[PDB]
Image (spheres, coloured by chain):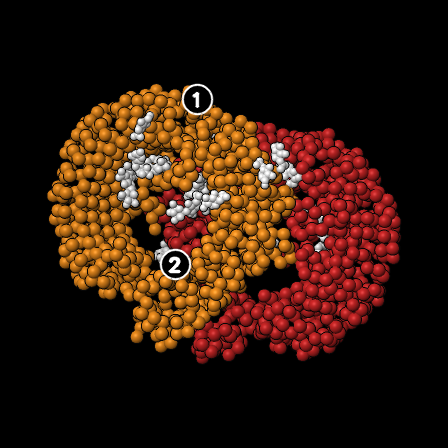
Chain colours: A orange, B red
Amino acid sequence: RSYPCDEKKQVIAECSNRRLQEVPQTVGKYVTELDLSDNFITHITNESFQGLQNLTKINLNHNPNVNGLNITDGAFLNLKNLRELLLEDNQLPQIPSGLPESLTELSLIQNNIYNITKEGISRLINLKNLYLAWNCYFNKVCEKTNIEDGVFETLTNLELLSLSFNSLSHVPPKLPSSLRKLFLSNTQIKYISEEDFKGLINLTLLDLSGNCPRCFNAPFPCVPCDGGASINIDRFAFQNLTQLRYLNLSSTSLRKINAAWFKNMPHLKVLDLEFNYLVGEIASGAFLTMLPRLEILDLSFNYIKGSYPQHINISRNFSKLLSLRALHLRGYVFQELREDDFQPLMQLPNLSTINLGINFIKQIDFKLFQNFSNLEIIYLSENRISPDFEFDPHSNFYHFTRPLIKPQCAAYGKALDLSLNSIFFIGPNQFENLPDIACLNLSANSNAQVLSGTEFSAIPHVKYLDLTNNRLDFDNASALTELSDLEVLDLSYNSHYFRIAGVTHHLEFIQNFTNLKVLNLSHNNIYTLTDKYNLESKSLVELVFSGNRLDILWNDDDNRYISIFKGLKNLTRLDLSLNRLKHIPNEAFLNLPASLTELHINDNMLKFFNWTLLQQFPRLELLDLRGNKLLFLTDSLSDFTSSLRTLLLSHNRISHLPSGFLSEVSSLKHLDLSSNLLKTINKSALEKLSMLELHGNPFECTCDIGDFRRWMDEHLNVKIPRLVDVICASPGDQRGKSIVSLE
Amino acid sequence: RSYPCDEKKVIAECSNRRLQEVPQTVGKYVTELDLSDNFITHITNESFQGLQNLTKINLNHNPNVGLNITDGAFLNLKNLRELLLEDNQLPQIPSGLPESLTELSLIQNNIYNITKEGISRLINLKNLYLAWNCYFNKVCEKTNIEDGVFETLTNLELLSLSFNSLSHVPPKLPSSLRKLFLSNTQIKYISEEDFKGLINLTLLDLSGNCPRCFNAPFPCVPCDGGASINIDRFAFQNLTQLRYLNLSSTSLRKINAAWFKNMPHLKVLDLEFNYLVGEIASGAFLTMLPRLEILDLSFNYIKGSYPQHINISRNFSKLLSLRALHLRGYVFQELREDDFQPLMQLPNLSTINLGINFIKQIDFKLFQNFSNLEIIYLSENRISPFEFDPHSNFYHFTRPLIKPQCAAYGKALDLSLNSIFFIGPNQFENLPDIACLNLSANSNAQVLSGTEFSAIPHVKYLDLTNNRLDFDNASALTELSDLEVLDLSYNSHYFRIAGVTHHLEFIQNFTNLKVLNLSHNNIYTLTDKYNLESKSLVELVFSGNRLDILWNDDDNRYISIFKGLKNLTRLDLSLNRLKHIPNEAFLNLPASLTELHINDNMLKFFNWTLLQQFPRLELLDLRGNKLLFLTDSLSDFTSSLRTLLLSHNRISHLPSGFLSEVSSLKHLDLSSNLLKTINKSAKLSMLELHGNPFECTCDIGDFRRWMDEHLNVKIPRLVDVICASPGDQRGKSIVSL
Ligand SMILES: Nc1nc2c(ncn2[C@@H]2O[C@H](COP(=O)(O)O[C@H]3[C@@H](O)[C@H](n4ccc(=O)[nH]c4=O)O[C@@H]3COP(=O)(O)O)[C@H]3OP(=O)(O)O[C@H]32)c(=O)[nH]1
Ligand SMILES: Nc1nc2c(ncn2[C@@H]2O[C@H](COP(=O)(O)O[C@H]3[C@@H](O)[C@H](n4ccc(=O)[nH]c4=O)O[C@@H]3COP(=O)(O)O)[C@H]3OP(=O)(O)O[C@H]32)c(=O)[nH]1
Ligand SMILES: *[C@@H]1O[C@H](CO)[C@@H](O[C@@H]2O[C@H](CO)[C@@H](O[C@@H]3O[C@H](CO)[C@@H](O)[C@H](O)[C@@H]3O)[C@H](O)[C@H]2NC(C)=O)[C@H](O)[C@H]1NC(C)=O
Ligand SMILES: *[C@@H]1O[C@H](CO)[C@@H](O[C@@H]2O[C@H](CO)[C@@H](O[C@@H]3O[C@H](CO)[C@@H](O)[C@H](O)[C@@H]3O)[C@H](O)[C@H]2NC(C)=O)[C@H](O)[C@H]1NC(C)=O
Ligand SMILES: *[C@@H]1O[C@H](CO)[C@@H](O[C@@H]2O[C@H](CO)[C@@H](O[C@@H]3O[C@H](CO)[C@@H](O)[C@H](O)[C@@H]3O)[C@H](O)[C@H]2NC(C)=O)[C@H](O)[C@H]1NC(C)=O
Ligand SMILES: *[C@@H]1O[C@H](CO)[C@@H](O[C@@H]2O[C@H](CO)[C@@H](O[C@@H]3O[C@H](CO)[C@@H](O)[C@H](O)[C@@H]3O)[C@H](O)[C@H]2NC(C)=O)[C@H](O)[C@H]1NC(C)=O
Ligand SMILES: *[C@@H]1O[C@H](CO)[C@@H](O[C@@H]2O[C@H](CO)[C@@H](O)[C@H](O)[C@H]2NC(C)=O)[C@H](O)[C@H]1NC(C)=O
Ligand SMILES: *[C@@H]1O[C@H](CO)[C@@H](O[C@@H]2O[C@H](CO)[C@@H](O)[C@H](O)[C@H]2NC(C)=O)[C@H](O)[C@H]1NC(C)=O
Ligand SMILES: O=c1ccn([C@@H]2O[C@H](CO)[C@@H](O)[C@H]2O)c(=O)[nH]1
Ligand SMILES: O=c1ccn([C@@H]2O[C@H](CO)[C@@H](O)[C@H]2O)c(=O)[nH]1
Ligand SMILES: *[C@@H]1O[C@H](CO)[C@@H](O)[C@H](O)[C@H]1NC(C)=O
Ligand SMILES: *[C@@H]1O[C@H](CO)[C@@H](O)[C@H](O)[C@H]1NC(C)=O
Ligand SMILES: *[C@@H]1O[C@H](CO)[C@@H](O)[C@H](O)[C@H]1NC(C)=O
Ligand SMILES: *[C@@H]1O[C@H](CO)[C@@H](O)[C@H](O)[C@H]1NC(C)=O
Ligand SMILES: *[C@@H]1O[C@H](CO)[C@@H](O)[C@H](O)[C@H]1NC(C)=O
Ligand SMILES: *[C@@H]1O[C@H](CO)[C@@H](O)[C@H](O)[C@H]1NC(C)=O
Ligand SMILES: *[C@@H]1O[C@H](CO)[C@@H](O)[C@H](O)[C@H]1NC(C)=O
Ligand SMILES: *[C@@H]1O[C@H](CO)[C@@H](O)[C@H](O)[C@H]1NC(C)=O
Ligand SMILES: *[C@@H]1O[C@H](CO)[C@@H](O)[C@H](O)[C@H]1NC(C)=O
Ligand SMILES: *[C@@H]1O[C@H](CO)[C@@H](O)[C@H](O)[C@H]1NC(C)=O
């Protein structure tokens, strides 16, 4: 049984974030990939891996976690098959000397390396990917980056070079022509000469973002080119970049795009022009002629500060972008979207996504979207429609790359996102002349209206409706029923009226949906309903009821809600967490749908749980009771269940395991007992279980512990994670140490 | 040193201490004993034997999480006046309670039988509480009141019987009564005989008898066919001294004016939760109330009905003494000027409350034409551009409608929890001279520009919390020259977004601004001006923001973010995720500070030597962090520090000399840390140590010795200052060795 790492085959040794002080000498001979990131390793020497000649990869990132990792000349030199070596965030002062010449990936992102030397690098002929980003940047106290002449020239298999967020001042000379991707973002390069990318006939990606940056409102310390000038790109800079697919020129202070940049660039797929000053160019846009194969165009945050124009001015020459799939125009900042303003786009055959987030737009003429060929995502979030390093070095710096629309919503069809606006009620004609919308997000519009069964009549086929973070007033039982096809409904965070005991709350409308599969009512603080105390639906499969007040609903002095979930005949998944529950009336538990396969009651305050009532739940596979105050287990659990696969009891107050509880239920694969109060496990508990969790428990590590230890050896198919977290509370000398390490 | 209680001046506070039974170590000299919320299971004549000067006993909520009392167990207690036995699941009144009893509370038990044997022996009772013994869907018997049981109680002033099944006003009540409480007692009928003889009654509560049950937040049984309570027209005839009358939720559709004939001093009339819409618009009984100060007609809405207007009878103009009119939940669309006519000449009408009416429009000019409103309460409308506490009102909350700190300044207008998502140019035309304005929770997303409040320029307290304000203009709120308190908490919406502007410059422009709250805005980036500046400002709350990011190691722009706050005495930096504070950032905090909070962050280290630049610093709060050790040189860094809070850190060892370092140091909190000892080595008035894991061997004795030799050093919760080790000491307070 491996220690300290968790070893598997897919041979990986997961060994991260385990407070290891030195490289463990206890790693299998057979491991090919070792991860020791986020540990406290302070030294590496020609000893540190002596056992492990079959190592293809070592991750040593972020050591030591909260001064600097200390690597000896040739410490890795003995590792003949070492391919990928990650050394990020290790406060290195130089590139380690004597690296094995077999390397293909080297990463030194986020260290203190300001000298890139032949001695360090030139001998590594097999390097494919080399990452030196983020060594000198912002107001980090650091030197200008010295790149020794010809250091890269010998790297003739190098496909990816990244030097971003270093002070370079000039594109380094003598780059090998093997290069496919070249990242030089935020490098302080003012000027790009015809010579800089001369040879690079294989380049597919070039990133010159952040050189001559647009600094207004920068969320980082930002230094403009003198006068706020744009980057200066020679007319012929890109001449031989025939294979370029991706070009990032975000925040280079462009007022003018040169069309001839693109003359020899027939395969260009992505042009990123965020954070420039391109309002003028968006109105003119000759360069657009040059880009009929472009799929993605990001023109976000090019606004003129202070200027809030009536309309957006889009060149007719947008019509020429025949391959365009997505257009991003956040942050142009304009008051009104009129049908004609988007004419140049209405015939683009493959234009699927339009993103106008964050434009402070007050009005939109929605009939305009109809006229589009093929829109699948209309993203209008964040407008004014009405009735220890801050930046991840492995992320895009200029936007977020999460999907615009949850995938679960977009699978249903056309998507319209009106989240984070001011649509505080939906009027009669609000959704008029819209397309057949299937996925609709109205989250956080502070919508306080009484829905009544007509508001979505124009878009009756909505299948996924996100109404979270509003303040909806449920005083009408026809609400939403115009949506016969509704499958998913998200009503989380509409507490506003639910908190007020004296106003009606009608949730009757739920029964009227033929196809409703998932319903989210979390964080609504539900403690009182009007007239009908029961949730009913023949359809519903999942109910999420976390963060309401079942403590008040199932209070011992009130019977009204004793069956609140019973009418949910089709239910398999129920979540009752964060309901302040101290106990559940037996009658109320036995009234939970008998169809349940998955029940969560975690993060309440349960002192007692009545295990026997499980008998009314033949199909129950998973039971989550984490984060309650549970004191003991039943000793005959298999009397009460034959289905239970996963039982979670982390973070309770269990001090004893009953007689043979390990082998109590055959069906139990996964049992979680971590962060409880076990000081041992007697032979008593001995007499299909894949995983058993035990970390956090205060173990008494005397010879009383030997029974279980023996058990661990006799059942190595029972996985016990985090063995370094399965710790002796006592005795004094054994305190801190893993139970697994003492004789 | 008292144990296990904390004795004061002579009051033994001994509640919530996990006591299995009454402690036998109670100071013999104690008057009041609090043992509420322990796990006590039995009381005998043995329990309180040694204590004879007992005025009062509290044993509520025992055992907490079945209180057996023996007959006559309290008999030996010759001076016992007050006895609290709430929430003990008693099956009967206990027998043999002493005669000296002036106050008995038996709220929340299982007592269904009120007996002479229990009660009639208690000649001296002023106050008797028997409420909440059988109610709702509790399994309980109808309540038996033995005939005449209260007859002998001729000093009885308060009798509370609410929330029990009575069905009739028990007969034969001592005429001493000032206050009779009979809410939710299932009494359909009030006869002429029921009160007749109670000539000193100032208060009568008949609420919840024949309840209005629609949308009730509790299991609710109406009288047959929604019928009203039946009150005999001479039922209140000899109730000449009545000041408070509660008829909430009695299903009244009609009020008999003549109930108020002999009652010309009624001050409070509660008519919540009935059906008095017609009565409100006709209302002869409004003539019979010339001294009435507070009238509550809330929640008399007709369900479904949502009328254009509110119909207020002319006769409201006879309510000459009216100070506060509560008209929640009438439910209607539009408040016109003509509709509040009757109200305009009432000289003392200071408070008008229309919360929760779903109102869409108001003619704000109508409030001018009143004689002297101090409080216009319009929260929770549609304006645009055991569950229950047995010591609270059942039908409304009793907290001030407007926070006292805001009302203190003058006329107040509360428009919270509406949909005023921007303030238009006339939103505040025709208003009185408002001094306190609440616009919280309106989802207002506007760019304030220094003109929106011109029509009410003397606002001194402005609550704009829970909005989504867009700070894109340095002149925001600058028309309010008199502004003293500005609360902008919970306006994260746009501060989240790196790409839009965030202009806080406007703050320097106020001569008289004292308090600024910017909590929970997740502020991490600001536009152009990176500094907060004010000559006047005295307190800044900045909790719930991102100083971890503002003060990041690779950015210098915010290193002086608070320096320009030259007059500042209180600064809150809690909940900012700070793992460490740059030294140059700390030194840049205003030197005027007297109080600094940096609790609930994640600090591993603290540069104590930095305290030399803060010579007026009295309170330093570092609770809920990850500090691993204290300086050993504190005397050298500060001579001003009185309170030092380190609760909930990871401190393992107390530095030699620490306990006698500092002269200014009154109060030191080290509860919930990792102290195993306080070795001999290590103005002091209080020292908190509960929650630490002490080694309870002989090493500990030097500290015990220390405790004895300094009784002037309070150490609360000694019950909770527990041993972790060794195995035979685990569990035991460190005094009990
Ligand atoms: N460019 C951009 N993208 C944003 C923005 N806000 C959200 N996003 C989303 O990032 C996601 C990643 O976009 P990004 O353009 O940064 O990177 C793309 C594009 O550069 C590129 N791509 C993607 C699609 C395509 O048709 N052609 C193409 O070249 O492949 C990357 C991987 O993204 P994937 O599409 O596989 O998730 C997109 O998923 P999205 O359709 O929901 O809108 C995108 C934003 O402001 N700008
Ligand atoms: N009656 C009533 N009061 C409500 C309601 N909602 C909030 N409140 C507030 O609770 C508070 C308590 O009022 P309530 O009528 O329940 O009880 C009063 C009144 O019954 C009575 N009183 C108060 C003032 C007075 O002039 N005359 C008078 O008889 O003494 C009690 C204590 O008041 P306090 O000392 O807390 O101000 C008031 O302080 P408030 O001015 O903000 O408006 C009140 C509500 O819906 N109804
Ligand atoms: C400028 O524009 C280009 C957009 O083409 C950006 O390149 C993209 O950079 C991200 C972040 O490093 C890369 O994503 C990462 O990819 C690796 C490898 O597959 C994976 O380990 C990470 O988790 C993450 O997915 C992405 O590959 C890359 N795009 C392409 C086509 O290679 C560039 O980041 C932009 N520059 C800045 C500063 O925003
Ligand atoms: C309201 O509850 C719904 C339903 O539970 C939440 O949406 C669901 O969120 C879960 C994860 O939180 C999604 O499951 C995940 O699927 C992904 C991708 O396939 C998988 O990688 C994850 O391990 C996980 O299984 C689930 O698909 C999603 N369901 C739907 C229908 O969208 C929702 O987040 C809740 N709303 C709020 C505001 O919290
Ligand atoms: C019916 O209306 C009357 C209006 O007076 C309400 O009477 C009030 O009842 C509350 C609830 O206990 C009393 O509050 C208590 O005041 C005493 C003062 O010594 C204090 O010790 C308690 O902690 C508690 O705060 C309040 O005094 C009382 N008002 C008067 C003038 O006595 C009554 O509660 C209403 N009934 C229901 C069921 O809501
Ligand atoms: C925004 O910050 C202000 C200033 O901290 C908060 O208002 C202040 O709230 C405290 C209590 O948290 C008040 O002090 C308390 O006063 C009461 C009554 O005098 C007293 O009983 C307490 O012992 C304590 O002294 C303080 O007066 C009050 N300040 C003002 C100017 O009203 C405010 O609550 C914060 N807002 C939010 C939404 O968190
Ligand atoms: C509806 O719009 C809201 C608001 O933008 C989306 O909420 C975001 O969701 C992502 C992923 O769930 C989170 O990481 C963000 O934190 C959320 N933002 C906020 C402000 O809450 C929501 O996901 C959208 N719904 C769908 C179905 O796409
Ligand atoms: C402004 O309006 C809101 C209306 O809710 C008040 O916020 C409430 O404050 C009370 C008293 O502190 C709290 O107990 C409530 O929980 C708060 N409710 C909400 C929804 O936040 C606020 O106090 C009012 N401000 C002033 C100055 O009176
Ligand atoms: O927007 C509105 C308008 C009126 N009502 C009415 O107010 C009462 C209490 O909520 C109910 O009868 C309901 O009809 C609402 O709930 N919401
Ligand atoms: O409501 C608005 C309208 C426009 N802008 C403008 O948008 C840009 C980014 O915030 C800035 O120039 C600002 O003037 C806003 O910030 N908020
Ligand atoms: C790191 O360790 C090496 C030897 O292992 C030593 O020569 C060197 O001085 C150390 N450097 C630091 C800064 O610890
Ligand atoms: C673009 O849309 C056309 C139809 O207008 C379709 O034939 C073609 O397959 C689409 N192109 C891609 C790459 O999806
Ligand atoms: C629901 O609202 C509609 C629209 O006004 C109305 O016709 C209907 O009567 C309402 N139904 C209920 C349950 O009140
Ligand atoms: C909703 O379903 C119920 C049947 O349970 C029915 O009474 C009602 O008319 C339905 N309303 C709509 C709009 O489908
Ligand atoms: C029950 O749930 C299943 C999904 O597992 C679904 O196919 C079916 O429609 C549901 N039953 C009814 C009556 O809707
Ligand atoms: C109004 O209040 C004042 C001051 O408390 C009081 O003296 C006066 O009698 C009241 N006026 C009336 C008409 O009740
Ligand atoms: C703030 O907005 C007002 C109103 O639009 C305008 O007059 C003023 O110039 C603005 N001030 C700033 C700081 O831009
Ligand atoms: C606020 O004060 C600053 C300088 O202290 C000044 O620049 C600005 O014009 C002032 N604004 C207003 C609206 O008074
Ligand atoms: C500083 O605060 C104190 C107390 O509020 C006050 O006396 C003084 O006016 C303030 N100073 C200035 C310059 O506003
Ligand atoms: C504390 O700050 C002072 C002043 O900057 C500095 O001299 C000292 O080194 C700091 N000490 C620690 C513990 O960092």
Pick the quarter of the image with the C terminus of chain A.
Answer: bottom left
SS type, badge 2: loop
**Residue B680 position (above or below residue A378):** below
Q: Chain of mark 1?
A: A
The residue depicted at 17 percent of the width and 62 percent of the height is A50
Which residue corresponds to the image point at 29% horizontal and 54% vertical from the top-left?
A62
* Closer to us: A689 or A315: A689
Residue A38 x %, y %: 31, 56
Report how far apart the C-alphas of labels 2 and 1 lie in the structure. 59 Å
The answer to which quarter of the image holds residue A504 is top right
Residue B217, compared with residue A286, is above or below; it is below
Depicted B261 relative to depicted B61: above or below: above
Task: Determine the secondary structure under disc 1.
Answer: helix
Q: Is residue B569 left or right of residue B266?
A: left
- The quadrant of the picture occupied by the N terminus of chain A is bottom left
Most foreground residue, B104 or A668: A668
Residue at 55% across, 28% down: A428
Q: Locate residue B11: give its quadrant.
A: bottom right
Q: Are marks 2 and 1 on the same chain?
A: no
Label 2 C-beta lies within 8 Å of the nearest ligand 20 atom: yes
Q: What residue is disc 1 on?
A: A339
**Residue A423, image x, y percentages:** 52, 33
* Circle 1: residue type: Glu
With A119 as the anchor, is B612 left or right in this view? right
The residue identified by callout 2 is B605
Looking at the picture, tell me which residue is in the foreground, A393 or A492: A492
Q: Is residue A124 above or below residue B302?
A: below
Question: x, y (%) of residue B549?
Answer: 39, 47
Question: Of residues B133 and B589, which is closer to you in this image?
Answer: B133
Is residue B135 visible to the viewer in this orientation of the structure? Answer: yes
Three-letter amino acid code of the residue under disc 2: Phe
Q: Could one spot residue A426 in this view of the protein?
A: no
